[PDB]
Amino acid sequence: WHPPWKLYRVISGHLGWVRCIAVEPGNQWFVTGSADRTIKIWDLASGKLKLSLTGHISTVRGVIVSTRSPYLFSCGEDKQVKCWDLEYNKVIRHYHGHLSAVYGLDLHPTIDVLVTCSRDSTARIWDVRTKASVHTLSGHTNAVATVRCQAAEPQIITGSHDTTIRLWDLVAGKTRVTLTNHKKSVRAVVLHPRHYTFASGSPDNIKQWKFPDGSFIQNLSGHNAIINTLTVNSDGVLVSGADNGTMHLWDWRTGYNFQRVHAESGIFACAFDQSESRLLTAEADKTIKVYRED
Amino acid sequence: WHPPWKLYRVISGHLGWVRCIAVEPGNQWFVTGSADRTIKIWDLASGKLKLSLTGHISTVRGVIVSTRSPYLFSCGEDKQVKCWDLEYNKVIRHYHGHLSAVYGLDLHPTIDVLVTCSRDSTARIWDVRTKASVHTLSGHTNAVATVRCQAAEPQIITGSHDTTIRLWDLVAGKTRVTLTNHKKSVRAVVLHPRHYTFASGSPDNIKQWKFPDGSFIQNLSGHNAIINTLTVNSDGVLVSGADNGTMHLWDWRTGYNFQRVHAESGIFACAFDQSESRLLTAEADKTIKVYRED
Ligand SMILES: [Cl-]
Ligand SMILES: [Cl-]
Ligand SMILES: [Cl-]
Ligand SMILES: [Cl-]
Ligand SMILES: [Cl-]
Ligand SMILES: [Cl-]
Ligand SMILES: [Cl-]
Ligand SMILES: [Cl-]
Ligand SMILES: [Cl-]
Ligand SMILES: [Cl-]
Ligand code: NA
Ligand code: NA
Image (cartoon, rainbow over the protein chains, first blue to last red):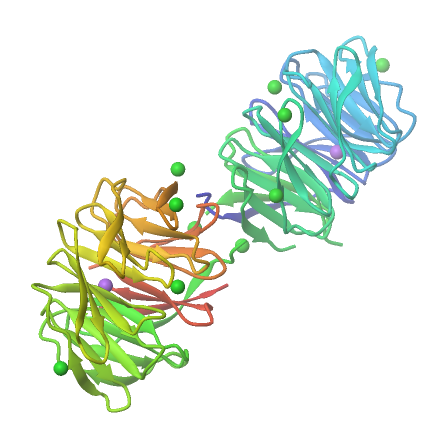
């Protein structure tokens, strides 16, 4: 059993769609990126604005906080990929290589690399401190909407507008497996924290798969909308956020949809805090909504 | 997904614990039995008292409405088993045979028999119109708390204080299979409407099994209290009612507990109406509580 989630706090300040959200490893603050071209750092406990980081010239599509270093990484529709030093509160590195808009990113848990995914149909692997390109993961035939890393092989998983999922060999920089089941564009991928399974979302279905080869488990059906985000906690609460503002909460193992949250409406990104007691959403109505168990 | 259930109406009138509840085939009214020794007929739409049937000298433990005839059957701790003619609103038949308190009953869907279960460790099969004993189902070593019928073999299923479930051959009047898994007294049995599976409840676990031989499927864990009742609808909503007043709602197939309803507290019996839109509970606080989807 998972207790229901209820709206606790609504955080405003952005002047356009909030496209991305991430929580720092120490759980003290969270970061958001927006269509207004800004990155904002908010205090988690209070919901107050700490800092506003400027530099992007188009929508900020991805934000992530480093565990290894006091860094924050961001990416945008302006093709820019930046490393922000959180001790100096300024950009220290630019990762050049994407041919068009950068849609998302992830950090590798064991290798000091940043992985970005783009409208250019690639995912790119960058050495954090030297900015050097490690590999350009080419194989998708359309925009790569989502990318996730893990320590175990396959180390990189991508979801694409080509309606496929690719499982990559990080060392060789090659596709190990291509999963074609989704009938429509894949915009979200989530890895279960126990490392045995993962899920992907498209309007036709949310699909659950087994590592390492991507054996299909089951469909999580009922969220008949454009799925923008998928996030899961250690307790097994899977959250699917849709472009029409709807949010479905599921039990990971059973695939059962336990809660349906009602809603320019839309949910672009979801994240749990480090304690997993708070669910933070980034929405089209220019706000961040905070949910807690009740 | 199953929408949550919320309290819609509270029906009072009984002067003691409400031990049993049943809905008529035409869905116009429902019947309850109580520790105050009365049987009450209430209008379903309004919740108003229609008739009060008197005759039992101890707690009424079971009530059921016939589909074949305009009859209502009742049983009690006074060892009495009665057939009430609903056209005349009076007792027309007494079924004699139980050696002690009668705990429950059920009607067979194809054979014109009434089945009762008792403190005497038996379940008894009675021909409705002649009152003749068809079979005395002996095999349990303690009180038989619950009994259910079905057209397919095994036609009769009993749950006992001996911690076992017995699957019976109605024709021979013999046990086909004895299920011993429960560590504690079994007080509730429910048959899934599709006829492939069934469930049983004890404080240690709610267990789900396959027909015809009772192959164990899974445990529905988390309702750590004395389970008095189990009821399921065609949509897959399983309701478990406890002696401490707690009610857990589950998805039948997955076994996932989706809702936990808070509470002399106690739930003795649960029943869905014919439309399955209403959940009616019979409680220790002397009331009938009506729940609807919200
Ligand atoms: Cl640079
Ligand atoms: Cl990992
Ligand atoms: Cl596999
Ligand atoms: Cl499936
Ligand atoms: Cl809901
Ligand atoms: Cl008689
Ligand atoms: Cl049947
Ligand atoms: Cl079986
Ligand atoms: Cl189990
Ligand atoms: Cl609940
Ligand atoms: Na993104
Ligand atoms: Na009963």
